[PDB]
Image: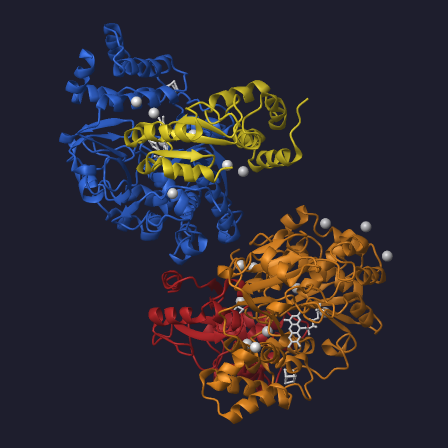
Chain colours: A blue, B orange, C yellow, D red
Amino acid sequence: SYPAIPRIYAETTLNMLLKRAKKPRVHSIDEYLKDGGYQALEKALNMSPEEIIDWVDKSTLRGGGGAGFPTGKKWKFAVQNPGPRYFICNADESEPGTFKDRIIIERDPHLLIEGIIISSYAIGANEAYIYIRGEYPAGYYILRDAIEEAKKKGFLGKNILGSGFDLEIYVARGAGAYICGEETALIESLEGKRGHPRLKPPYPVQKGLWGKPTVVNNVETIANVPFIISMGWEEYRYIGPSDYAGPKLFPVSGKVKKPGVYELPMNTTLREVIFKYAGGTLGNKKVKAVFSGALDCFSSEELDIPMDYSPLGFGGTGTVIVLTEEDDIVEAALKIAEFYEHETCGQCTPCRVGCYEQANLLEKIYKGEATEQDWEGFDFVNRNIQPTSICGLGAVAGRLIRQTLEKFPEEWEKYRKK
Amino acid sequence: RSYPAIPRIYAETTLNMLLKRAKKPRVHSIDEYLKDGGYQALEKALNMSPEEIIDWVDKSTLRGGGGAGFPTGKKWKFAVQNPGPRYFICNADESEPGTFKDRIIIERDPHLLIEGIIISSYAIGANEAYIYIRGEYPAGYYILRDAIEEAKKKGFLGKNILGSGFDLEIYVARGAGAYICGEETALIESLEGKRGHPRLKPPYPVQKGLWGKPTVVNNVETIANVPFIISMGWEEYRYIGPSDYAGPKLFPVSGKVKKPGVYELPMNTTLREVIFKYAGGTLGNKKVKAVFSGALDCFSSEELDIPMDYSPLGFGGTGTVIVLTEEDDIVEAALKIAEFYEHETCGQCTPCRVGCYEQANLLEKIYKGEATEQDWEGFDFVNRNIQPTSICGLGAVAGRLIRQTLEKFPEEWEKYRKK
Amino acid sequence: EFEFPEELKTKLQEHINYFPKKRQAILLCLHEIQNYYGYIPPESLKPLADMLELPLNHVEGVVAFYDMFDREDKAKYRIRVCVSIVCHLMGTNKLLKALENILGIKPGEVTPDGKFKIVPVQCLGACSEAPVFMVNDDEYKFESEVQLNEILSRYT
Amino acid sequence: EFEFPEELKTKLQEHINYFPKKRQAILLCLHEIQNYYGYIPPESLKPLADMLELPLNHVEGVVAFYDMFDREDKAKYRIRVCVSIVCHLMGTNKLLKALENILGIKPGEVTPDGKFKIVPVQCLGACSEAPVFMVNDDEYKFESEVQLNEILSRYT
Ligand SMILES: Cc1cc2c(cc1C)N(C[C@H](O)[C@H](O)[C@H](O)COP(=O)(O)O)c1[nH]c(=O)[nH]c(=O)c1N2
Ligand SMILES: Cc1cc2c(cc1C)N(C[C@H](O)[C@H](O)[C@H](O)COP(=O)(O)O)c1[nH]c(=O)[nH]c(=O)c1N2
Ligand code: SF4
Ligand code: SF4
Ligand code: FES
Ligand code: FES
Ligand SMILES: [Cl-]
Ligand SMILES: [Cl-]
Ligand SMILES: [Cl-]
Ligand code: NA
Ligand code: NA
Ligand code: NA
Ligand code: NA
Ligand code: NA
Ligand code: NA
Ligand code: NA
Ligand code: NA
Ligand code: NA
Ligand code: NA
Ligand code: NA
Ligand code: NA
Ligand code: NA
Ligand code: NA
Ligand code: NA
Ligand code: NA
C-alpha cells in the first residue's frame, strides 16, 4: 500500500521507457522479468566496464536533466580519475511543468534500478544513491520496495550474479529545495548539509561526494541504459534522427486536451507535440506561448522547431507548458518570478537580491501599484541576476521573463499605462 | 571461479542460525565464514571428547531433517556401540517434490555444512566422510569441491586437524537421477558403485553400512545444526522454540503463496502461520484447498492449525509445504504424485514395482475420462496394495497422499467417476 | 530535558544506520520527527544533533534551509497546495476558495483544532493534473468543492 | 576398437583415483563421458569397465538404472524440463509450448542439428521458482517466451 498519486496520462510511439509506465500502476519485479527485464544487466556483466561506456557513447545518449550533456562522455571523464567512484541518480525533479521522471519511478522502478546497476558497473562505483525530492513520498516507498525485490533476486548486493561486482543503492529524500537538483547542491545534501551549490571547477566527475569522482545522471537518462545494452548501440541509434537518437519523454501541461507524458523521437516538432499527440488546445483556442518549464518562452511563430538538443531546437527537459490566447503573459511571468524568488539559495548577492526584487517589483506591476522607478528597477534587476552567479539558477532566473518582454511587448505596455 | 547458473530462491529467518548467511543468495567463502566466527565450534569440539559431543547433541533434542525425524544423538550412540572403523555420510540427495531447503545451505553456506561434517565425523570416530549430492545439483557439487579445498588449505581437513590427532577426508559423490538414492541403504549401495537398490533392514547402516561397517547417514539440515549446538551449548539451543521440539527448522514453501521460498522458523509455528504470516498468504488471496507435504501427505484447509513439529498431530516430515488453492484440481494434482512414484520405484519388490506403475497408468485414464468401471475399481485396489512386502519407505507411502485426497475430497473424485 | 519516545528513537536509529555515515541521515530523521510530532519541536534538535554526531548549529541551519520542515505550527494534516505556474493557470484560486469554504482557513493558517494547515508550495511535479494538492503524503487533482469535501472527509 | 581420447582418459583416471576404491567413481566417470560426447556411446562402456575393474554388465546395469544417462541421443545441450507437481501447477505447459515455438521440438525430441534435446525430468529441487528448467548445468526459472528466447540464444 502506497500514498495516493494522480494518474498522469502517458503515451508512447516507441514503447521503450513507457512500455510499462504507460499503465498507471506499480509494475513489480515479476512483470518486469516477464518482459525480459534484468537480461540487459546479465549481458552487461559479461562485458567490460569500458565496452559499456563505449556503447553508451556511440548511442548518442544525452542527459535528460536539462543540460543535454553526452552521457558516455560524462562517464569517460569520471573514470579517468582514480576510484573509489560514486553514482547518483538525480530524482529531484522540481522544475515547473516537469513530471516526466516520476512516472518511471512510480510505475516501472526496475527499469531505473537496472539502469543504475549497469551504470554503476560501467564507472566502477560500488555505492549508488537515488536522491528523490521530498514531495514524491510514493516514489520513495516504491523505490525502497523495488530495491529489496532486486536484492532478493540477486541483482544487488555482493558478487552480483557471480560477476565479482558489488553494489548497494541508498535512497535519500530531499526536503523542499529545487536547488538540490543542481548536481553539486545535491551532493552537499547527500553529505547532510544545506543544498548550496559549489564553485565549479572542480566538477563532480573529478571531485564530488566526499571529494571522490561522482557521476550524477537524471532518472530518464539512466532509464535509457538497459535499452542500449539490450538492443546494442547501433540499433538504439536507428531510433529517431541519427544525431539526436533514441526516445525522449515530453511532459505536456496547461491548455491542451491531453496533458501528460509523451514518449517520442526528437525529430518531432513542437507543433506536432501539441496538435498531433496532445490533442490540440482546450476549446481549440490559438496557442499564445509555450513555456519550456521556467527556462524559455516560445511564441506561436516558433512552433515548427524540432524537439532535439540542436541550437534551434526546443532542448531542455522537453517540458511543454501551453498558454492560449486569453492567458495573461504578465500574470504568467509573475508566477515564474515567484518560483525563482522562492528557490535562490542566497549564496550569490545578485541572485539573492535579484530573484527577490524581480518578483517583488513584478507583483507591484501586476497589481497596478508600480512607480516609474519600480518599472525601471524591474527592467534593471531582470538583466542583473546572473553576475557572479556560481550555478545555473542565477544564470536563468531572468531569461523567460526577458523573452516575454521581447515577444509580447504590447501586453506589458498595457500594464505600464496601468 | 564461476559456477553454473542457479535460480535465486528466497530465504527468510526469524532465528538467524542456518540461514544467517544463506538468506543472502550467493556463495559465502571461507574468509566470510571465519569473520562470522565459523570453525570455532570445530576447535571447541576437538577439545571435547567424542562422547561429550554425542551427549550434547542428544540433550539438544536435534532430530533428523531428512523426513523421519529420528533423534540424531540416539543414532550416533547406536553407531558407536559397534567396533570401528566407522563412516559418516551427508545425505544431499534432496529429490522429493517441493523440497529445496538443503540446496541453499550447500550453495550459499557450504562451510556450515563442512564444519558440521567434521564435528559429526569426530564424534562417531569416522576418518572418512562422504557427501552424496544429487546429479541435478551441479553447482552445489562444484561449490562443495571448492569449499573442501578451502577448508583443507586452512587446516580444518586432512591429517592431525589442528594438532588434535584426528584425521578426516571428505569425498563428494554425485547421484545420476534416482530419487531412491536418498534412501539411506540405496545411497550406500550407490556409493559402493552399484545400482541404488535399498537393502532389507535390519541390519541398519549404524550396524552394517558402507562396506559392512558402522555408518551414520544424516541429512544436510541435520548436520548444519551441529556447529550451533557446540557453539551455544545444548541448553541455549534447547531454549529455541518449544523445549520438546527445539532448534531451527527449515520450511520450503511453494505453489500458490505470494512469497515462495525457504523459511527458518521454530517448530511451534503453525501451518497457517507458515502460509499466511510468513509466506505472505495465497496468490490472489484465494482460499487454501490443500497442502501437500511433498509427495507424502495431503492436509485439507480444516487442518491448518497444526504445529510444524514431530508430534503425532504435527506436520512432521521435511516441513515441505506445497499450497493448492480453491481452483486447483485435486485429481490432476494426485496424478502428478502418482507419476512421481511410477518414475522412482526401483522395482525390487513386486507390489511396489507393479503398484506404482498401475496407480499412475489407471489414474491417467481416470483423469482423461477413459477409465472403465474395472479401471476405477482396480485403481482403488492398487492404491491400497503398493505397500505389501516392501523393504523401504517408498513402497510404504506411494499410495498415502492419493488415499488422503480420496478421503478428504470425495466430491471432486466423484465428478470424475460420474464422467 | 527532552527525550525522544522509544518508538521514535528506534526509527531515528534505523535511518542513522542506513547510510555509510550517520550525518547523511539528517533529512530522513527530520522527516521522521515531523511525521511523529506534526512539526519539528526546537527542543528536539539538540538530542538529534548528538545522535548524528553533528553540532546543534549545523542541525538548526539545515532545518531553516529546507522548506518542508516547520518549527512553528503543529498540524495533523498538511494540505500542500501548488501555487506555481501550471496550477495557477488551471485553477489554484478555486481550490483555495473551496478550502476556505470547507475549513475556514487561508494559506499559512491552521484550523483551531490543530487538524489541518494549508501550506502553499512550488510545483509538485503533477502539472498535467493541475490544480494539485497533497494531504500529508497523499496527492490529488482538485476537481470541485464537492469532490474536495469528500477527499478531506477521509482525514480524521 | 573404441579408445578414449587422452584428455578424457586423464579425467576418468582423476575420478578413479579420487575415492578409496576405483569402483566408487563409476557415476563420476559416466557423467564425464556424457559431458564429453553428448551421450553415453554404447562402445564406451567396455573400456570404462576395464579401468573400473568391473564386469561390463555391471556397468551396463548402472547406465540403464540412472535416468540422467542417455545412450540413444547425442545432444550438445540438454534442456531438462521439470514435469513434477509444483512446476505443472505453476506452468510447465507454458514453458513446453514456448520451447516448441522457439525450437520446434517436444519432450523426447532432438533438433535436427543435434543442438537441443528436451528431457522431461522429475522435481529439480527449485519448486519456489517453478516452472524450472536446466540447460546442461545451468538452471533457470521460466518467466515468458521472450525471456526464454534470450536465455537460449546464449547457447551456440
Ligand atoms: C537549479 C538547477 C536545478 C536542477 C538542475 C540544474 C540546476 C542548475 N539539474 C541539472 C543537474 O545539475 C545535472 O545537469 C543533471 O542531473 C545531470 O544528469 P543528466 O546528464 O541530465 O542525466 C537537474 N537535473 C535533474 O536530473 N533533475 C533536477 O531536478 C535538476 N534540477
Ligand atoms: C524413498 C526415500 C527417499 C529419501 C529418504 C527415505 C526414503 C524412504 N530419506 C531418508 C533417509 O533414508 C534417512 O532417513 C536420512 O537421510 C537420515 O538423516 P536424518 O536422520 O534425517 O538426518 C532422505 N533423506 C535425506 O536426507 N535426503 C533425501 O533426499 C532422502 N530421500
Ligand atoms: S546562482 Fe543563485 S541558486 Fe545558484 S548558488 Fe548562487 S545564489 Fe545559489
Ligand atoms: S519398496 Fe519400492 S522403492 Fe523401496 S526397495 Fe521395494 S521396490 Fe524399491
Ligand atoms: S505547477 Fe502545480 S504541480 Fe506543477
Ligand atoms: S516440482 Fe519442479 S522443481 Fe520441484
Ligand atoms: Cl575450547
Ligand atoms: Cl491572482
Ligand atoms: Cl566383463
Ligand atoms: Na505516477
Ligand atoms: Na559503501
Ligand atoms: Na512519509
Ligand atoms: Na528537493
Ligand atoms: Na552533469
Ligand atoms: Na523464491
Ligand atoms: Na577458527
Ligand atoms: Na569432553
Ligand atoms: Na541456492
Ligand atoms: Na579412507
Ligand atoms: Na539422486
Ligand atoms: Na577430498
Ligand atoms: Na528421476
Ligand atoms: Na464432499
Ligand atoms: Na511559483
Ligand atoms: Na536442480
- Number of numbered labels in the structure image: 0
Give the image quadrant in which the ligand numbered 13 is located. Answer: top left
Give the residue at the far left of this rendering. Answer: A301
A374 left or right of A182?
Answer: left
Horizontal and vertical percent for residue B198? 67, 81
Q: Between A321 and B385, which is closer to the camera in this rendering? A: A321
**Residue A79 appears in the figure:** no
Residue lying at 24% horizontally and 27% vertically, measured from the top left: A296
Q: Is residue C26 left or right of residue D116?
A: right
Residue placed most toward the observer, C85 or B91: C85
| Image location (x, y in percent) of residue C53 | 61, 25
Q: Position of residue A376 (x, y in %)?
A: 24, 8
**In the image, residue A38 above or below residue B140:** above
Q: Quadrant of the C terminus of chain A?
A: top left
Image vertical order of residue A405 relative to residue B307, above or below = above
Residue A273 vertical position relative to residue C77 in the rendered view, above or below? below
Name which quarter of the figure residue A411 lies in: top left
Image position of C94 (left or right of D2): left
User: Where is residue A130, by image quadrant?
Assistant: top left
Residue A52 position in % (x across, y down):
37, 45
| Residue A292 visible at all | yes
In the displayed structure image, the side of residue A34 where residue C37 appears, left or right = right
